[PDB]
Picture 1 (tube, rainbow, N blue to C red):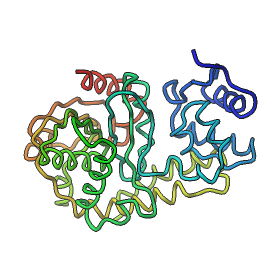
Picture 2: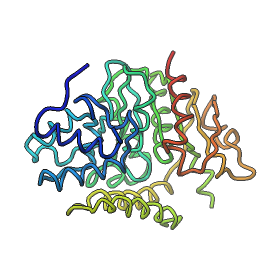
Picture 3: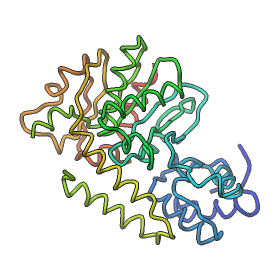
Picture 4: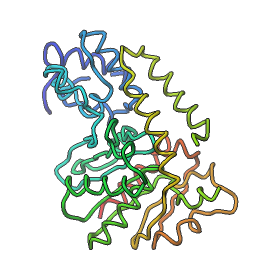
Amino acid sequence: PGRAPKAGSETIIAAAFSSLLGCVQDADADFFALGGHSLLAMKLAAQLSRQVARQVTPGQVMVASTVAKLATIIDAEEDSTRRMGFETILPLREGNGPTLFCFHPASGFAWQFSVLSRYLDPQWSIIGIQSPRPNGPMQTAANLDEVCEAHLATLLEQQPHGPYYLLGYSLGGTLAQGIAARLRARGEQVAFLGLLDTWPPETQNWQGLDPEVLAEINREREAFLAAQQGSTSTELFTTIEGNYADAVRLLTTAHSVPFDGKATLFVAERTLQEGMSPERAWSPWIAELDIYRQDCAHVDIISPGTFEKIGPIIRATLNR
């Protein structure tokens, strides 16, 4: 179906794809559904950038996962594509059916949710909710409640009526659960609330930028990204560092609210605390809980590997 790469931009993009994924044959080839991810996109962007003498960003690849779409981004006035992939709304995939809204972790970016592309049926749109800088809610919020309220308003703009399907990872899980609670108070239906190894802040606050390891792994991808030789831009990681600091700040102001609905929790078994089971931690704030234990650590709960099992479970849960 579709066409084959056109002369110029599309051809240059397809060749780039081939080099990375190991195979582009048509203009409608999706970078992520085939196996790509944000890091492999950072390579593409830097590659094409040095190749066409233009600022190509990883963010552009995240929202234009197609040879066709990315080609259009490069062909268009580069003054209108500067913030692509860095805005509140992150269109990972547009479908002609329901929408799964995915909430960002402490980094404020929802790029990691691209892993869902290979699992959700075609009709589904996969829309990430982010917190850009400056002026994203994480930066301007005095407390986490303010961030939940801001994202709720964003969500209602994107889809004014339910039912709603929400997915959150870590901090995003906290936000998703708080948003679900608010939607229910509005008499709206929450058909799906997915939590990727999310815990009530109360089971953690009873205890500053920590762990340092959280800054280490951030530094890990720091090098991974620069591995493709950062080309004059550092907006990505300065944004991440800034949001991390605010996430830490906000989590101390975090208080859970009761959600009278069912949540689907994916637990990272390797980092579970002896004595605090997921069922016990969430009992006061989630009415019904379906738990799926994964053999991984917290950080890897959203990894493509872990998702070889989580992805199908989410698809199965959503189909009904």
